[PDB]
Length: 132
Length: 48
Length: 49
Length: 6
Image (tube, rainbow over all chains, first blue to last red; front, side):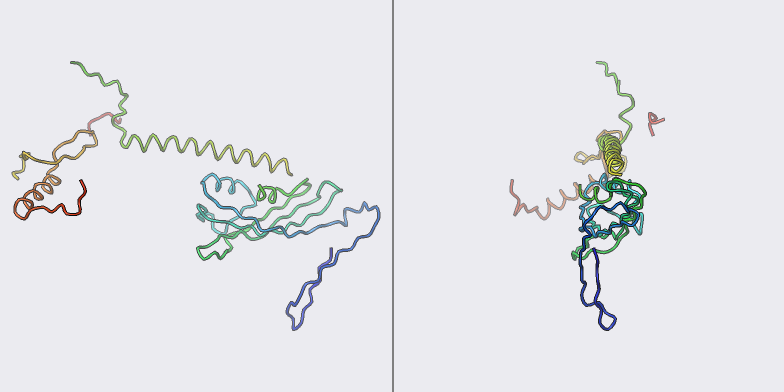
């Protein structure tokens, strides 16, 4: 998967994307890496239990610890970079991006950051959590 | 007629309802959050 | 109202102990209501009973 | 301690 960016007057104009496939049998997982831009996940924080679960997760890192999450709508704008050990097991997993709160105006505003990092994993536990 | 208070000084704790109700809330809250955080750390382990 | 005296009509306040004892202040509120009522009358217009 | 009369 390749991504171009055409610029004029040192300003971005359009992105090209092209995907190529070398037909064959390949073992060189040490030269394999994959970056994906996840869909934006949304959560309505209703209960003080909901917020306890989020604080449980190392990767949930608010700018201000004491931020009142109750009855707020968080959005999670997340990219996940991965490297491969083999076909199944990832050699490393990174998942980061801003956590935003919805205001009365419907404007989303950064209040913190997702920051997950890991070695040998079988999966991305941040996306799994946000999906469910 | 005799009247026997066999009420273990419970008369003396004020707002006995609000207090009773707080004790139950805090127990249930503690239980619920632990059960949820338990289930989720289990699944995060399983995914990884 | 002579202090030391409980009026023949009064209001009561609930003590933390849980008994209903005479309350000089509330009783004043009520007895002044009665005095006002006796001289000027009370209206009950717009009251559904 | 709670069963005095304050």
